[PDB]
Length: 7
Length: 227
Length: 214
Image (cartoon, rainbow over all chains, first blue to last red; front, side, top):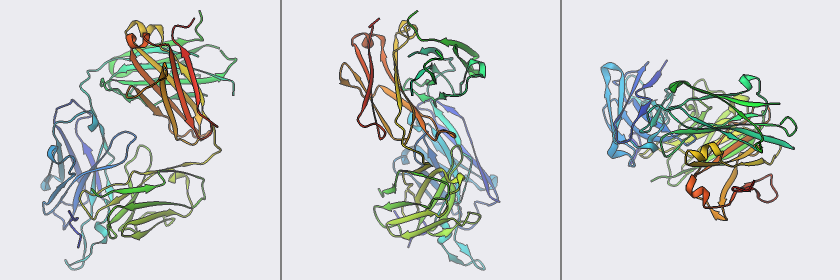
């Protein structure tokens, strides 16, 4: 899944 | 100044549980968005990411090791613990913990996330060996033969590391190559130490082997066989 | 999962050169990529974060560029401390992958290995095991391939090898490979061969012996 700070 | 340091057992036996502790200073795991992760490096191999934990307590794990890892933090002691269960020999590696910055804030307002994209400070790393061996001294065997000649000693079946090898009580150094030991499937190490000399010197050659762990010193003179 | 491929895996260079290492991702990772330099015996050290930002205290000869799926690290003027292994790391998707690494070592002239094969000692044989060792001495570049053959059968899964660190005077490497068999199996064959492939050798060289021959 996406990193904690992505998007 | 941020510093981290790993601690735990240097040796662990297969099926056992390994608990590694990362103690740090210079930041708090209560600081905004900070993370502490664990990365390992088997000897001679690439870095491998294991897990990370943030100050808001979100945890993430390598999918390949998910079932065997638990990461936890103890904010008041400035420590992060990683527990790996059911270890096997392939888990032998140097284990590092590392700091991950949280976003930069301005008057407590997050304004830059670029600093989270890296693990910026690392601990020295702790070497962990997984083997079911008890301490044991090496058996030393001879290795016997541009027009250079080669000979050496095969330091076989010992545990744990390290062992020291020199030639002619320390007087022979040029042309000496002592290779890093390999951990055999048996759980014992093995290494060779060789030396190259002008095909004429065949002068005497003796390897001095010393495995402190088992109190085993051996001097083995090696020559060009044939009586 | 996401794949990070570094190129080249190994690279030779000299002090003062400009080198560039590249890292490609299987899916876009935006700018969430970091570069590290790791010297032997030490932990990796952060050079560049967020694809191109220079980490504080890191010398300006290091530079990083790119975003999406292709990134590059360039060291403009290589210094002695830069002979090391470099890694890139992606932090956009979990797990936070590392590339395979690229080793940067001292360039020198190609040198083929001097190869030697050692039969097991009678002393070891009495204990029931047989170690056959092959030595590849002072060669360059580092990549070398050793293939054991017993009575022409290709061996597999029964050997181990280790390589020395680049020699500080020679700039060459040496490699030791051990073939291990029970005394019994050992006794069931005659021709023990160590086949070596290397850039400095026009074609593969084979060193061998016939067991028990006196």
